[PDB]
Amino acid sequence: PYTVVYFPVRGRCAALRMLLADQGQSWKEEVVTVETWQEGSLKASCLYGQLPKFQDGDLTLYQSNTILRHLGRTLGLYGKDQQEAALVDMVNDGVEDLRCKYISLIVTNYEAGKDDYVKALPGQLKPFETLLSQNQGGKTFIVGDQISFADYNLLDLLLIHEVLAPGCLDAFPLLSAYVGRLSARPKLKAFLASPEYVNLPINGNGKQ
Amino acid sequence: PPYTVVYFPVRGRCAALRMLLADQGQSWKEEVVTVETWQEGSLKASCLYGQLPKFQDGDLTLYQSNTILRHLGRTLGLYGKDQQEAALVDMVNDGVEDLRCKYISLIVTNYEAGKDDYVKALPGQLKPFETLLSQNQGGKTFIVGDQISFADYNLLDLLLIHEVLAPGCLDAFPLLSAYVGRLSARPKLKAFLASPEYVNLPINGNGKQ
Ligand SMILES: [Ca+2]
Ligand SMILES: [Ca+2]
Ligand SMILES: [Ca+2]
Ligand SMILES: [Ca+2]
Ligand SMILES: [Ca+2]
Image 1 (cartoon, protein in one colour):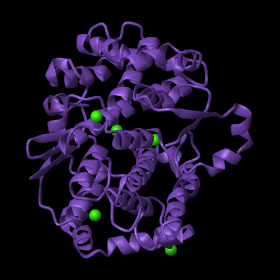
Image 2: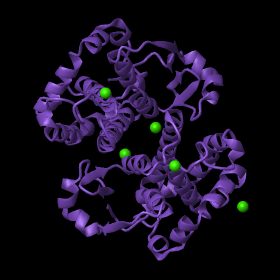
Image 3: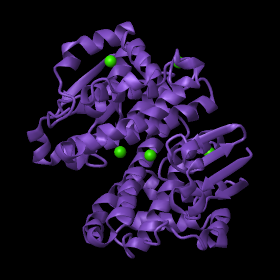
Image 4: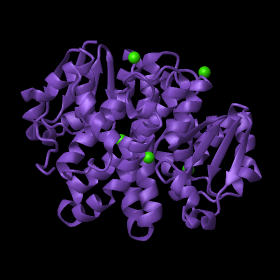
């Protein structure tokens, strides 16, 4: 069974939770208070001193993208073949890059950086619109014709950017329609509407 | 195959995948991109994320160095023996990428002011890899399991460039030290590391190391 060990935020666990919910998998949440984290003991035991920590039976993993790839591999959300698997990675790596820029903004430079960030945003989102346009006219998934862990990550990234810069997908019809389509998947829709998702802040510092 | 690496004339983010290809007896073409070519803008606008490396494997075109590493890992069987090991391989590689990102940020943006703080923090950043080795066959084999993975090549490069940045940074870490020596001695890799193709490239594009 699966355990997610994280702070009481959506953050870097939002995509992997969406994945698990949408795939109908059961899991446990272990919540780490800022104070438990400050004590230092748990942090010292984490491979790279960070959360999330994830348990799959006796397998303990760190790094949100390691967890996504693991779930992608085990649950068959990693493309139909080797070529698609590579494209799934290429998408997820691009999502991670933009996520890192988003995190940097939220944590270190929200006030002085937001305008610079939002104006730079369309150029950062365009590659995903491009990928969609080259795959069945953008009517299905980011890679190929079945959902992948990259879809869940990309979906999260887009949802949080809509909160940051409302209407930012107006310039991107395929990304816009993709957000609506994936968000409407019944198990995912239910999860996104649920107190367990809605009552967590996006980020620890309460900015979004 | 065939394989083509499209990149600046630097080691940088292609060093690990080149070591991987060389050690695995694979052949590849280098397409070198000069400053003039990159500044012209055409190549850059054609890249998915506006970045190099670009990698060609037959009709497949890839961007993102870790995507290229994972692809070569997948297709060449350098990804652990099973799913549990593959997850550990990813965990190592994501850790390597995190420190590489920090290394690049120093080199490119903050070398003069930031070097002291970086080298001071370095031991705490390397210790996880020593720990991983200690928990896998007493550090006598690879970073994960009993066979080489793309993570080994990436970690090896990370360690090598760090020894340039902070000579002696592995002295306190016997497993990491022995690992660098052991992997660096693999005959095809040893030959590649000794070759002008590797030796005569700068680590980074701005001449800092
Ligand atoms: Ca599937
Ligand atoms: Ca990247
Ligand atoms: Ca609108
Ligand atoms: Ca093998
Ligand atoms: Ca990371």
